[PDB]
Length: 192
Length: 192
Image 1 (cartoon, rainbow over the protein chains, first blue to last red):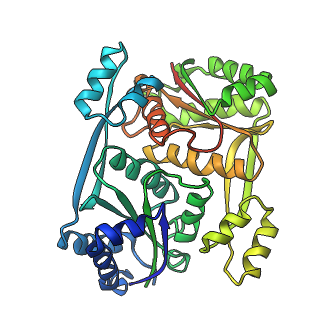
Image 2 (tube, rainbow over the protein chains, first blue to last red):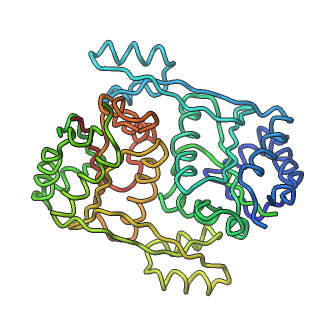
Image 3 (cartoon, each protein chain N blue to C red):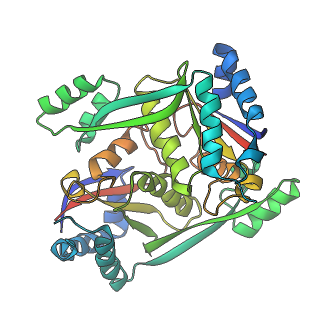
């Protein structure tokens, strides 16, 4: 496959280029290696595409990651426990006489404190990846930068209706105003 | 039904109380009027709950709204056209030699420049409502404040697994850091 567009959010790409140059080179090579034709089961299959990326990513040591945390109804306690370890979060919340509720986020591809999301899903999933998933791993000190691989409109239009595309998601990010979300990111738009 | 928790984001609630006091009173009355028991088709049905709120909301003049816009791959052009009318966005993007792509957002309940989302859906939909939907209507100058009505965990646990709850979504918002999203909001957690 090929990269058509790349957007560096909060200079996330440059951070990778300085501190983890091998990662940027690898991400680029993995994309080139994906055979989109074999996924043309003539629309393209999101399941087939996800399987192809999964094999290549895991073949290069990108592995699953999970981050646990405790939520609560109290805004003050949330702000005071965001950066704490799970057990400490619960301890602090309960010590204030408030209820702690178990939660977590899980992602398939993490390596060298970089998370990569390959998204060929419906319109609501990218928003969730950017503002909740990547942010969760970032705030929990598991990643320093997140990467979102998305199909350009030229590819999404050749897939089932309802699949989000690069141009639309880039818009959703920039529409937030400067520097939102707080996690540095690299948005990559691809095509066959 | 009853309100258990209320969170004013960027002082959104106070904005309503000063400029639109009748709206806050009405929202509170609508919630009280909802018969959660009749939706206990003993778990609670999200479809039944959504139908009950829809009838009460529309009965009070809350109506659908749609906002159109043109996205593009060019970050600079996006920032320069965010606040423009749709036709002007396309004109500006194309005048720079870049492609404009049609898009939009639609919501069921808008009145007096306030949007209300009643969410009893899966984990990814609230994120989309907050960071994309409410923000789209806000940036397009259709609303000044957004409202998100969510079930507290005590209610969501009595519904199908996978339904987001107040405590979890409040966490997702505060985890962003101060003032994100840029649109003022009122988060309301409810129970039977």
